Amino acid sequence: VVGGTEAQRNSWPSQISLQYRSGSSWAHTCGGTLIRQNWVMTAAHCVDRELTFRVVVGEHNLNQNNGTEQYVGVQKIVVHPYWNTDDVAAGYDIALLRLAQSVTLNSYVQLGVLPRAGTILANNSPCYITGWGLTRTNGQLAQTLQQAYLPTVDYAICSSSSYWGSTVKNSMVCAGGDGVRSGCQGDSGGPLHCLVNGQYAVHGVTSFVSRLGCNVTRKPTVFTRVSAYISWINNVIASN
Ligand SMILES: [Ca+2]
Image (cartoon, rainbow, N blue to C red; front, side, top):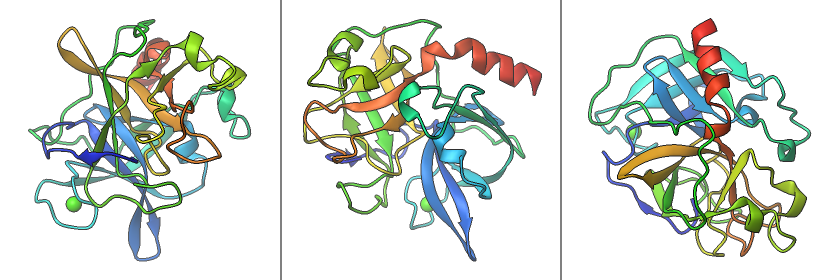
């Protein structure tokens, strides 16, 4: 997250870190949202590589013992069947991970609340992106979980020519674009939390930014629109 502030430890308890085994250690690669005690919602593109993955819940600082973490292997990966790795702009950047064990809920570990199916946010709705991704374009991952206030940019504006044009689909949510604050590599798969009727819900799964850089004016961060996938999500969890 570029232009973020450090999140309080208990603000976003559905945020997870998706990590892959790298030698004798584990490397953060993406965010995710805990949606059942044994299912995480993330981005399809985060799990294209043939890696060994684990999820960490109750995580705050990737580089130090927080006293709150639970580490769990990934037992099954269900990518949206329409996803195509060579075409992020087509959409469908969403995947569910069934965890090998059910995690224990507490102040640091809670299920993310999802929007009702089809819900579209009005332009300029208040949302926060969270994650441990790069804190600058071509920078380094965050140690501590970061948040950045990224108001939505509606489909009409976002798909206009000076924004993302044809690249953005109505199955996506755009947010930010101010040239200062944005997601960045390593935030993919994580939540966009938006305040609606007094309650935060996870409206986006972080998907992409500009090839030109993370924080680029009129290139808001782009997210898979969670509310486009409620039936798909329910179908997967019920069949698995
Ligand atoms: Ca930690």
